[PDB]
Image (spheres, coloured by chain):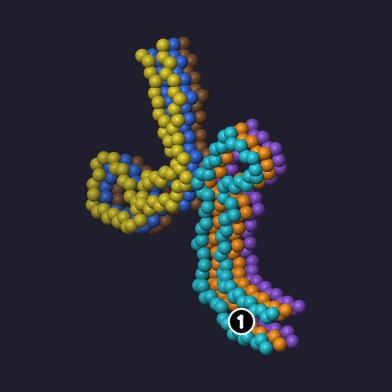
Chain colours: A yellow, B blue, C brown, D purple, E orange, F cyan
């Protein structure tokens, strides 16, 4: 018999949130390549890639798992 | 017998949210390539790629799993 | 016998949301190539690609899974 | 004898006038009432009311009063 | 005998006027009431009321008063 | 005999006027009341009330008064 009971609260009362500035890669990226030999797979990423700005008004994260075996 | 009970609250009261600025890759990317040999697959990404701005008014994330075996 | 019960709330009361600015790749991307050999598949992405702005008034995410075996 | 004089000038050279935002009550007003008793007159205002935006290109005032007895 | 004189200049050379934001009550107002008794007059104001945004390009104000008795 | 003379200049050369933000009540106002008794007049104000933004391009103010008796 398996009878867990949950009454949880996960909460936020953020009054105000703002003036957030993220300015990644604001300079120069200069790449010069000469006479290279590549004998296998190449991945190349140049510049400003995958940058995230993430500003949730809540962003509360409640994670749970149950098992029998 | 398996009877878990959940009465959970996952909540936010964000009063106000804003002035979020994300400026990825605002400078120069300069790539010069000469006399290169590639003998296998090439992936190349150049510039400002995959950048995210994500501003959910809640963004609360409630995740759960149950199993028997 | 399997009788899980969920009475959960996942909630947000965001009062106001705005002035979100996302400006990916606002500079120069310059790519110059000479005398290159490619002897297999090429993927090339140049410029401002895959950039996301995502501003949901809720954006709350409730996820659940059940299994028997 | 009473013979007062005024030759005054009231002036402005406001070159351009604009980009004015007035945004009252942009978020939730939530009033919840149960089992109240009122035994005399009620005046009740709920929401956004009586808010003023007033943007005259002049808006100067010249006000004067004279009296005898 | 009564012969006062005014030749005054009241002036402005305001080059440009703007980018004015007034945002009263962009948040939550939440009012919860139970089992109250009122035995005399009630005046109630809830939310965003009587807010003013006054932006005159002059707004210069010349005021005067004269009397005999 | 009554003969005052005024030659006054009241002036501004404000080059530009702006970027003004007034943001009262961007947060929570949360009011919870139970079982109160009021035996006389009630005046109640809740939220963002009476707020003034006042931005005259001149706003110069010349004020004068004269009397005999």
Q: Is residue D61 visible?
A: yes
Give percent across and percent down for residue B17: 48, 47
> SS for tag 1?
loop
Q: Which quadrant of the figure contains the N terminus of chain E?
A: bottom right
Q: In this view, does C28 lie to the left or right of E22?
A: left
Q: Which is more toward the observer, D44 or A47? A: D44
Q: Tag 1: Cα neighbours inside 10 Å, few (<14), some, or many (≥20)? A: some
Q: Which chain carries label 1?
A: E
Q: Which quadrant of the structure image shows residue A8?
A: top left
- The structure residue drawn at horizontal position 39% and vertical position 23%, both measured from the top left corner, is A65
Q: Which residue carries the number 1 mark?
A: E8
- The structure residue drawn at horizontal position 62% and vertical position 64%, both measured from the top left corner, is D55
- The structure residue drawn at horizontal position 57% and vertical position 70%, both measured from the top left corner, is F59
Q: Which quadrant of the figure contains the C terminus of chain E?
A: bottom right
Q: Is residue C20 left or right of residue D32?
A: left
Give percent across and percent down for residue B31: 32, 55
Tell me if residue B45 comes above or below residue D52 in the rendering: above
Q: Can residue C44 be seen in this view?
A: no
Q: Which quadrant of the structure image shows residue C43?
A: top left
Q: Which is more toward the observer, E54 or B42? A: E54
């Amino acid at each position: 018999v398996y009878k867990p009971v949950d009454l949880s609260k996960v909460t936020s009362k953020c009054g105000s949130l703002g003036n957030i500035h993220h300015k990644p890669g604001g300079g120069q990226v200069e790449v010069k390549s000469e006479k290279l030999d590549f004998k296998d797979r190449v991945q190349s990423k140049i510049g400003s890639l995958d940058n995230i700005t993430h500003v949730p008004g809540g962003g509360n994260k409640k994670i749970e798992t149950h098992k029998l075996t």
